[PDB]
Image (cartoon, helix red, strand yellow):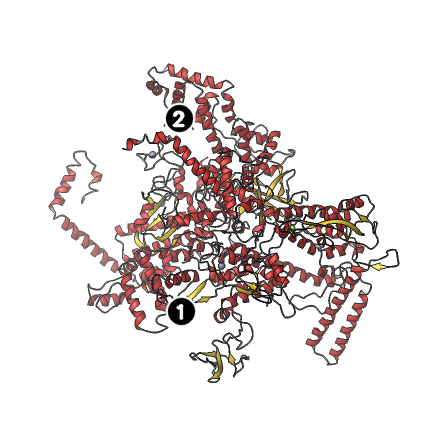
Amino acid sequence: HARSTGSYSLVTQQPLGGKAQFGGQRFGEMEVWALEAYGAAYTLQEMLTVKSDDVNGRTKMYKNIVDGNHQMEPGMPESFNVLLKEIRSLGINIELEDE
Amino acid sequence: LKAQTKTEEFDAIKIALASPDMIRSWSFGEVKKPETINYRTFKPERDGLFCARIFGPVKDYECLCGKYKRLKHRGVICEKCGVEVTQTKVRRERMGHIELASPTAHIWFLKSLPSRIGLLLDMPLRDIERVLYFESYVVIEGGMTNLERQQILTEEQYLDALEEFGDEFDAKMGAEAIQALLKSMDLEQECEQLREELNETNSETKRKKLTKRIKLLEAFVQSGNKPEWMILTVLPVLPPDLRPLVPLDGGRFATSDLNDLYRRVINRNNRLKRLLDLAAPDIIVRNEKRMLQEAVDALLDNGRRGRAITGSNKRPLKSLADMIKGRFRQNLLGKRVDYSGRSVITVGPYLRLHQCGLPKKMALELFKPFIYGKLELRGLATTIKAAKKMVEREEAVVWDILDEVIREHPVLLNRAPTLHRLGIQAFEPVLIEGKAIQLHPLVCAAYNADFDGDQMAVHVPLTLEAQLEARALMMSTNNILSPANGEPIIVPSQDVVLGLYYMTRDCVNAKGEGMVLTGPKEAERLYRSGLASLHARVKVRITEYEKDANGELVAKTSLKDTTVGRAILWMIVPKGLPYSIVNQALGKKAISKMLNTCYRILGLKPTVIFADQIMYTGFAYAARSGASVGIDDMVIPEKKHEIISEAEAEVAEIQEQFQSGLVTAGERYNKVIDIWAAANDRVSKAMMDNLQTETVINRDGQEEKQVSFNSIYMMADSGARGSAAQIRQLAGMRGLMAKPDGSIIETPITANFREGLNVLQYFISTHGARKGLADTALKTANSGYLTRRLVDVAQDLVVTEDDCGTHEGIMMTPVIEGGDVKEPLRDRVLGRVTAEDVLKPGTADILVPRNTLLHEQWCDLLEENSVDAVKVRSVVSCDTDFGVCAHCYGRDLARGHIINKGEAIGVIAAQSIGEPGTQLTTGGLPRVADLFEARRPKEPAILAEISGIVSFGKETKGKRRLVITPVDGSDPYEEMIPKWRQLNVFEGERVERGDVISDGPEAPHDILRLRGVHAVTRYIVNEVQDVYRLQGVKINDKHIEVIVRQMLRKATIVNAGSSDFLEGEQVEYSRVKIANRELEANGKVGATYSRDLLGITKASLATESFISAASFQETTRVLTEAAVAGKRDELRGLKENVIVGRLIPAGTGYAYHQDRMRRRAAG
Amino acid sequence: TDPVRMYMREMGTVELLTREGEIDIAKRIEDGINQVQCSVAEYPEAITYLLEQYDRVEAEEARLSDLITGFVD
Amino acid sequence: ARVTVQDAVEKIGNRFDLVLVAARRARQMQVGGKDPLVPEENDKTTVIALREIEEGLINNQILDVRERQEQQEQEAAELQAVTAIAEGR
Amino acid sequence: TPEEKLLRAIFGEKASDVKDSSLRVPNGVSGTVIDVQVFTRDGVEKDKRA
Amino acid sequence: DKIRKVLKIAKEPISMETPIGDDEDSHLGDFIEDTTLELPLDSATTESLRAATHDVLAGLTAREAKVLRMRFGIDMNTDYTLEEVGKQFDVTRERIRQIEAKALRKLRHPSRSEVLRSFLD
Ligand SMILES: Nc1ncnc2c1ncn2[C@@H]1OC(COP(=O)(O)OP(=O)(O)O)=C(OP(=O)(O)OP(=O)(O)O)C1=O
Ligand SMILES: [Mg+2]
Ligand SMILES: [Zn+2]
Ligand SMILES: [Zn+2]
């Protein structure tokens, strides 16, 4: 199996795999430690931002790849952005501070 | 400078209570109807749980009514339906709210184990609930009458107490009461009460609970939160697309369970709002209020009441709280990733070390966006739309383009259980035909990859950084040493070490015996021409090099006494190595130390290109060898049946003694097992005597015997495959088996695999096999749960400071276990940096001066002299607050130099410990957990508490007291000792504090307390290492020592003058503040403390960042207990920075956080 | 706890009505509503406004359904 | 230089700051800012930046010196234009 | 979009009300067709090949 | 025939948190893909069809752009009825219809079309 860019799930903007290019590889907690044990800070960020949950960066990436600029403009994963609204839709006020 | 308003780069995250005013800021309308969609048109009913007025348009830039469909109209609200025309995405962002009729208690603050609403009031839960369901009144600011504030009344009592005091006395019931209680409550005033009460009454039962409550209370005032806010007046609703109502095929619908939960709250709230305008009897509205309370509770956290079930379906409904979990460690289970793939992996021995075979097809799909760009960048495609149609057509030219994008572009490879950092390594891709992934055979050892069906996954480093990160950090050839023990993880495995062992071998009389050859080149010429045999004693002129000069290769040429094979192998050995390194027999043992020395002498590159040539030549000559395995290769000794009958005789006599009552049944079973155990040892080293040497050959004369050249012997002697324990099961008899309950069966398996086993033997062989598969299956689980507990206590630990600057360090010796040296000194001390100058057997003479990194030269300069002990700086002593100085840590890495700033030694320590965890066996892997968890043993020994002469006091009262009496100081120490446990202290001897008063195991908690931090850290490492060193597992003490640093992360204060008296806290925070007190502030009001040993999971429980804690701990309690404190998470750490999707505060990201933490708290 | 119990328990204290007590309450209900009706009838603005609203019914500014539903007989 | 990075880490001691400096240089070439400082054996901008470290002619200090130089070259071109923003007076 | 409509007026293609949803052979696999079955809901007229 | 339409909506919607029965305890909702989304392999070409038509429109006479970008929605709010474009340009109506036709005509010859045509498939 392989997959560059494919389909994505509605609730969690994460790679789901139906028709055409299949589902992506799961990159679990233990694989994350590997990158942490290396210095792979960027390899990790792009692995859990632009390459998966970042609904905006993922296409700012695909456009930048074909443009010939190997940059990522990150942004925030949807998993955490949903957790804002999930915590916030309990009685809990959770904010992002400073500047 | 201007402040700011909008959106820049956020740092930190604050959590708090939400005022009802706060909750309405998020809402863009009140949901008023339980309606969802319309039912014929699947449009959203306005003022419903799904709505376009409140949340957003259904499709992009289209008003709901339709009068404003054009993308021109944007910030416009249609005059009919209160809908602005933006993206459908805002149905994923915009929240709503509901105005509650009656106040409603927040289940989390009412019911999370320590009731916040409870102890904020100092009110019990069975009382608050009794007030909440309208069963009994509670007083509120009862004033100067007959009743206290928190007093609780019944119906009749409230009536009797009302007739006496009409006003000037207030009592309510229901949520309005508890809301008033928290509202009227004054925190600062109650603070002044708890402070005077602490000082007036001296009692350990009084001021032990007193201090425990007040720390939350004044944390609550300082929090900014308001106590009224735990009673909900407004309930915010989650955006709809996060609980959507999408259609499926066949026209059937699916929706999140919240909609059943949200619908019910609305219905009961609306019904209650009706029951008030109908002015219903209180009996009804009370029941309605109770249901609204129940409905909200099942929405926020279903499960803490009677657990409502979903519509028509038996399963319960997944509440908001369960949206967050979904039990433990539920936000960090993993995320699927773009630009990835997997397939079955196969060999490919032709590969250089830094590359891997990638299928033509996988590499096509994986780099698709690179190909699309590189295609029209050169102009082979007009535009991207045709570029797709090209690589869809697989035109011949896209293949030649794919090589262009592929060249300097590494890929990542990952195998299933990712144990240590080597489980993901970056290789340079080689375009290969077929659907298999080709894996370099030397990197197999790191991955634990067989080729029996195992698969690996691939990942594309997209950004420029990740490509350089993959190239400089994760590359195959940049990690050739294990980070668990500075030895090479890229050892020749099996097929290859058989080859070299076959080369570097010699037989007594072979073709070429005795000729003299000008150089190694003519030695290969002699073999490939069929003139000289690969193994024949032969003198050859060789030149070797040695860099004994100041960095320069001195050459030396001689006629060395070797063989033809070892001559040809010398053509591979690079430059400054001695010819002695190949002059021997070269088994897997000697073949890896050959590789190690090349790295420590010549450096990285010449080692990488070496390992390749060792594999190429190893494979080739192993294939030339024709080594096989036939049935006649497993030689059974001729004396086997003899040994069996002899032990078969002894047992018949031990039985003879048992019949006559000479020996016991327990002795018989024990004595019979011993003669069978001996017989197996006898057959064993009988077949190995025959097998190993019986090759009797002849050179010019009569006879002469040597190590055998039989196939299966060479496999073991070399170390390629096979082990003497396993071989013994083929020729000799195979052991005694264990019957299920744990006994070992008194008649062993006399037969072996070269013969047959019979029904009975095989049937008994079964239990060992099945419990083998189960034990090895379970101990693969226990390990994985260990490395979790281990990274959870570490993770955030990073080499931060350069040199903390200390002379503190642990005294390093060889372990010398009873008999002789179970571990040399040179191993324990290599790669560490010395605490102070080490001296010769005589002094005035520094041999290594102060903090120098003891490497191989220094270790020999140590091993030349008779130095038997070296004080070494250790992580447990590194005085860096928040992290570890590079010096005190050591050097180890997959690279050979001292640790670099920013590496996340916390993880790579934990990994190195739990990776070999599969291979262990009180003792075994739980014995490791017992130590790291600091678990006290069942029946401990007690240690001498204080120095002085000891004596016994009182008599037997269940406890026999012991009174120690120091020479100078106070003597009031008396310890209650159960005197039915045999003691060891001499009853008239002066005892030194920390000595054996009884015997048996000891608690680490004592060791730290009595003998000190340096003794407990020694006790752990030597005791866990005994588990690993028993199983033949090399783990440097370094890694165990960083875990220990986390175990004693905390301390308890003894004296005061600044903060509390007994609190437990980090030495990092404490030491940072009593160092702040030796100058500045007070002259020295500083406090003394006492280091506290925590088990890893207890030590991991204490994390500042609540986002980290909400990962693995119980997410409800962390979120509640943090939201009441108004706690700020500053990020800073590892776990949370992953959760929020930004650069790790380590590695390449360490430079980023260091540039960020400094701009913060500055201008 | 669980509201079913405490509702069941709360109303179980209420005693069933005798077949005569049903009339006692319906009589007290009669008095109260009739009492306010006698008080509504004493208010001049209540007379003028009912006349204000009927001068709205005869000018086709409403319907007879919007003001009354019937008289006695 | 493509087989291992050890020769480069010698010139900048961190192994981590090497990935950050060599990446910062790789952008200067890929996003067509600059031309190489060493002959390119087809090597991508990933490696060419790494060759420039082993050759010793590029590091974070040398880059910042050249950049702070370019701040003043483009400032002297825009010079006679931005002083014409004496309309704020 | 604007630009796509300009593309519709230049090369004059009657923009379809219909989307391509054909069953197509999965990528990579290849073989021979050896059977076709058609099950038509009762009431729909059995098509030609059916 | 309404029975079918009736029978469709009579089924209550399905718990999206239904366990689907895998070994990962996958829930139903984890499998419903986002069909409202534009795939990056498409949005990439949208950013390319942009630069395509912009280059092809600078190959026209200057007032052919302002008359074409006005007839379609390109780089302006809304599209303009060709009469509305006529009021902007003094000489009105039929005059504009030929400016419209001739601009598509200069772009239809295989020299300016070679780039644009490959957006049709
Ligand atoms: N990171 C990985 N490294 C090596 N092997 C992997 C990896 N991931 C999956 N596999 C193999 O792929 C399937 C399971 O995949 P998944 O767990 O269901 O997840 P996803 O559906 O998203 O692919 C198994 O292989 P097999 O089915 O052949 O059977 P096996 O487990 O006994 O080897 C796995 O070994
Ligand atoms: Mg295998
Ligand atoms: Zn509208
Ligand atoms: Zn230190």
Label 2 to label 1: alpha-carbon separation: 77 Å
Question: Is residue C8 in sight in this rendering?
Answer: no
Badges 2 and 1, same chain: no
Q: Is residue B1045 left or right of residue B535?
A: left
Query: Quick one: SS at disc 1?
Result: loop
Please name the residue that numbered disc 2 is placed on. F73
Structural crowding at the residue carrying mark 1, measured as other residues with C-alpha within 10 Å and reported as few (<14), some (14–19) or many (≥20): few
Name the amino acid, label 2.
Gly
Task: Point out the frontmost of discs 2 and 1.
Answer: 1
Quadrant in the rendering for residue C60: top left
Point 36% across, 23% down: residue = F80
Q: Along the line of sight, which residue is nearer the eye, D34 or B23? A: D34
Q: Where in the figure is residue B362, as x and y percent of width and height?
A: 60, 39
Q: Is B1131 above or below relative to B638?
A: above
Name the amino acid, label 1.
Val
Please name the residue that numbered disc 1 is placed on. B1054
Q: Where in the figure is residue B445, as x and y percent of width and height?
A: 64, 51
Q: Where in the figure is residue E43, as x and y percent of width and height?
A: 52, 32
Q: Along the line of sight, which residue is nearer the eye, B773 or B311? A: B773
Subunit under mark 2: F
Quadrant in the rendering for residue B87: top left
Say whether marks 2 and 1 touch (CB < 8 Å).
Answer: no
Q: Where in the figure is residue B1017, as x and y percent of width and height?
A: 52, 65
Question: Is residue A44 in sight in this rendering?
Answer: yes
Q: Is B948 above or below relative to B382?
A: below
Q: Along the line of sight, which residue is nearer the eye, B89 or B602? A: B602
Structural crowding at the residue carrying mark 2, measured as other residues with C-alpha within 10 Å and reported as few (<14), some (14–19) or many (≥20): many
